[PDB]
Amino acid sequence: PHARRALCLLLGPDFFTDVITIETADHARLQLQLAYNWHFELKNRNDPAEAAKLFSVPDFVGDACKAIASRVRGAVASVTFDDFHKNSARIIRMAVFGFEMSLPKARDQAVFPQNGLVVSSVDVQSVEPVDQRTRDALQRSVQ
Amino acid sequence: SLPKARDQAVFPQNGLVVSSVDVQSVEPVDQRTRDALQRSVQLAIEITTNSQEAAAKHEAQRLEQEARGRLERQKILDQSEAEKARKELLELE
Amino acid sequence: LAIEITTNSQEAAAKHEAQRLEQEARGRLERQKILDQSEAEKARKELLELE
Amino acid sequence: PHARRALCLLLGPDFFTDVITIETADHARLQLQLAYNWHFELKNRNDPAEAAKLFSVPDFVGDACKAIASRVRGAVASVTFDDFHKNSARIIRMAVFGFEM
Image (cartoon, rainbow over all chains, first blue to last red):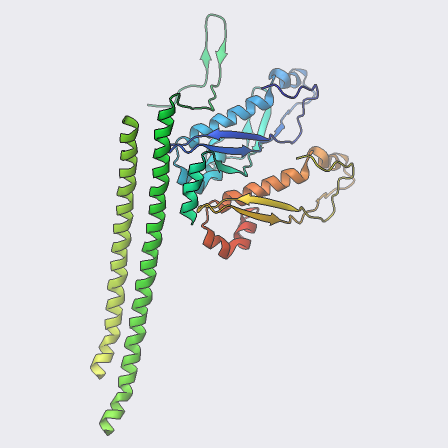
């Protein structure tokens, strides 16, 4: 909640080293890491009010990560795990922002009107079930 | 849009508004509830293992039968050709 | 008990889906069986007339 | 996450010694090494703004490797292992970028 304290609020292209515990309709406790490729869109840099709207949030990383976390977990909770382990990267990136683009694939941009924060990409690398016996049983599935 | 709700919760007493409500930890309190629904996942994973292996067996029997049918095809061709020359063999016999 | 009854419901739905896939794949397999037998006996024609 | 610290940001043709753990639809935990032949395209070298856009990232190698990592793992998670061990080099290199050619 409060670990790093610095005056230099980074706004350039960067990321968030985030990991989340989630549950889907079939209840296998799963922990996933998120990347949250983010940057700040300030269309009028010289504007004092719009520049001051940047610090309206006290924890931009916290708000963004928890919001995308809720968007992940609520949508996964409506999918079964085998469909999830089949089609995760798609559903997790479509449910967190946007709508149909081509039913169809989602966008690749997540704007926050409170401050100007935007998340461009959400990368995932570690889909790992939490319970040991789940992984033991699905080891049988592969074997 | 029955339909989806709004994304704003105004409090007229003071002017407070709640825009979003995020949730990350749906956790049952009782231990035995989680123990029992651990069984639900441990069975519902195995049923889909049965589904995928049943699909694999279906594919295997499909390949078996199609290769077997093509093999009776070439069997019929070979028998017909062998008895094509069994003609000359048997007329001059 | 009411959690376990819905576990039974979802596994019953899964079994229904499994028997549906079984029967449809089996029916398509009799389809290709009929095709293969008809074709094999199409050449069993020439085999048997010249036999 | 933060191992090498140097002012000389290399932009010439080079690579990334990367290894990734991935999972596909049939769950056999697999570890693969990646090379990531990379270089920087700056079409207007004299442009100060475009040259300064180069350092907009603090970890270019980290962002590139993790992005290609997600593109690998999400696509493999939609393929069975025997098809994967059959046709890996194709699907892994097609899913990470681009479209049909």
